[PDB]
Image (cartoon, rainbow, N blue to C red):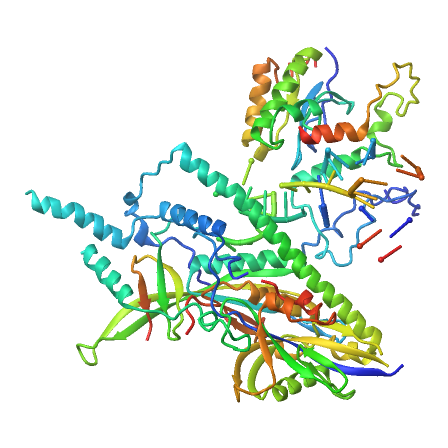
Amino acid sequence: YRSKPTHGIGRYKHLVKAQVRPINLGTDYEYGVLNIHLIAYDMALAESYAQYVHNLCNHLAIKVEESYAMPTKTMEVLQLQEQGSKMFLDAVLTTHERVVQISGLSATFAEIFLEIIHSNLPEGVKLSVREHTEED
Amino acid sequence: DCNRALLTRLHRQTYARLYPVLLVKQDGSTIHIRYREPRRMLTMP
Amino acid sequence: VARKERGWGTVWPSREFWHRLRVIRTQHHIEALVEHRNGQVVVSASTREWAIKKHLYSTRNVVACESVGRVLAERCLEAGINFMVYHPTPWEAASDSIKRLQHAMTEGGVVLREPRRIYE
Amino acid sequence: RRAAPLGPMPNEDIDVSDLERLKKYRSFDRYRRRAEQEARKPHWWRTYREHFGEESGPKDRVDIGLPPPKVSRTQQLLERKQA
Amino acid sequence: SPWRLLGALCLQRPPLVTKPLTPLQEEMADLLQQIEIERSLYSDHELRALDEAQQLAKKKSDLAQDLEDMWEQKFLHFKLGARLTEADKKDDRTSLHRKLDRNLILLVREKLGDQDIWMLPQSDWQPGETLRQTAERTLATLSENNMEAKFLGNAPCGHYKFKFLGAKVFFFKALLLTGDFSQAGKKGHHVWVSKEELGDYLKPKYLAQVRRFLLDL
Amino acid sequence: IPIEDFITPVKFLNKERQRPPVELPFEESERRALLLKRWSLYKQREHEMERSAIRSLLEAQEEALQELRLSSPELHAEATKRDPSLFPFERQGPDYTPP
RNA sequence: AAAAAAAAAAAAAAAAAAAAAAAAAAAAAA
């Protein structure tokens, strides 16, 4: 009640707000909107390392925005048969891809990050650093 | 640290039998693919 | 015949009771209390109390919740109070530690669900 | 006509600038706890406690006791630890 | 207060092939093997194995084995590259092909006019140059090799000062993609060394702290 | 234009009959449980040592960069910026048998 | 000037998060 010392006690909504550019200043240098593509043949492997990434970022205070799985790519591999000369034979594979997006960075946290990233890389796992623009 | 995230099972609720497979791409390198066919090995040309 | 506190009902939990079971579960220790609406805790069973602490193992366990339960139960009949109300949380009420808490109190001889008022 | 807050205003301490970087309680529970913590301090505004007869509030206790049993700290701490 | 400017570089070789497992990681491995193949739903191989194992008996009273044996022999017939290219030589600290499992680093041997220097490779950067430029330049020029190395940042790893004059040694990290080493028998002593050896070979207290920002793995 | 692979395929519907039994003695249960607890302890020490490792690393960063600014201001103008060389950073994980 | 009060209140292990192991050395090493 406006005239009281206590006005605004209940007031909250500034507290919860329920309602892109990299900033490069060359000194405090914020390079944001970064895309980590985790690509591998094994689902369990992919999901595991993805998990590890996401959690790592959660602990490092670096803020993750979007963690999502990109479309799987189905490979058909044709192998030469020696008996029939130009005769082909076949075997099937699948490539899985996960993505973890970080909204903020500084030079020192990149230097630091990449280290733990490729240090802790699993066997049969391939890694990618990119920028936010891609098309699904 | 290579063994960090290497230890897992597939967490989906309903799924096929997954069997360890050795996979040779064209390097001389080998990978472990967990794949439904019991076959010990497969190799790409 | 006394007065309960009817009311609130905007908020939680219902503060209508003479006596309430208040179970506070820390990552370390289970502490189950008996409360009066004056905010004063009447009879309490805590794991940090050397008495139970020294008799059994692994403070956080289901075993320990049951424990603290029976402890508070006998301590209840000692206090003489047979009645206190318990308001679990929906996700808590379903959990085991609290199921068997409630059994420890039931078999203690203590009733939850305070008897109704007289000419309320 | 606006008045001036007397002492602390409850939520003033946390920074509204950059809410994303502030930690949250994602738990109903944590909230409940911190809440009751705030329910147990002496606020400068009319409160439940004030009207509802906390029974004299703070009392300086006239204590006619049997003086406390004297035992040693570190001894019991160790013994317990070993047990 | 004159400052002496010396660039420097931490040269990181990628660990190539994975390490075998801790006994506990192995017990956990087998454990997850069991539990995973436990919740397993059928198999195409196991369907055609068990259904035919049961059906051939009822064509008897009134395949999977083929494939199993074919694959057994086809895997056994095959042979693989060895896991140790270091210890069969067991000698070379100077081979860039030495350690497959761990991360490796370059050291160099120099005896200068007034000094005896065991050198984690160092550079001299002129006041106009950027630390970056001299890092790379001195890298490609010093070792007489064609080196593809992807650096991480424009920011440095770690800094160690020696003040006589006063002077700075600035260490950067270069992540090695593919090196080509020309004149593999050149006299200048380049020691490609693991973490444990980076402990031993290092005299200085400036280089004793590079194993502090190193990746221990 | 999103399509996930998360759904459970139609191939897996009626073949459900293949894996009904699972049974453990108190022994397998006990073994696996011990193994689990121990594994928790282990992983915890692992995350801890990881954290102190990267932390100490970051302290090498602290001492370094602060030393660089205390020495040359031109050097904290140079190296505090992030270079274009980081954009398409790509790295491949290790394999089982070397080429 | 001694676990991330005289024993307590982040962390880790059942589509990605999110929500049923521990503690200065013999008042007088920043």
Residue located at (92% from left, 47% from top)? D2
Q: In the picture, residue D30 is in which quadrant?
A: top right
Q: Is residue C31 above or below residue E103?
A: above
- Which image quarter is the C terminus of chain C in? top right
Could you tell me residue F59's position as x and y percent? Answer: 73, 63
Residue E178 drawn at (x, y percent):
52, 80
Nearer to us in this view, E147 or F6:
E147
**Rendering quarter of residue A71:** bottom left
User: At x 65% / y 21%, what residue is drawn?
Assistant: C85
Q: Nearer the viewer, residue C39 or E37?
A: E37
Nearest the camera: D12 or E106?
E106
Q: Is residue F33 above or below residue D23?
A: above
Q: Nearer the viewer, residue C23 or F37?
A: F37
Q: Is residue A85 visible?
A: yes
- Residue D47 percent location from the top left of the image: 84, 32
Query: Whole-percent x and y of residue A132?
Result: 58, 71
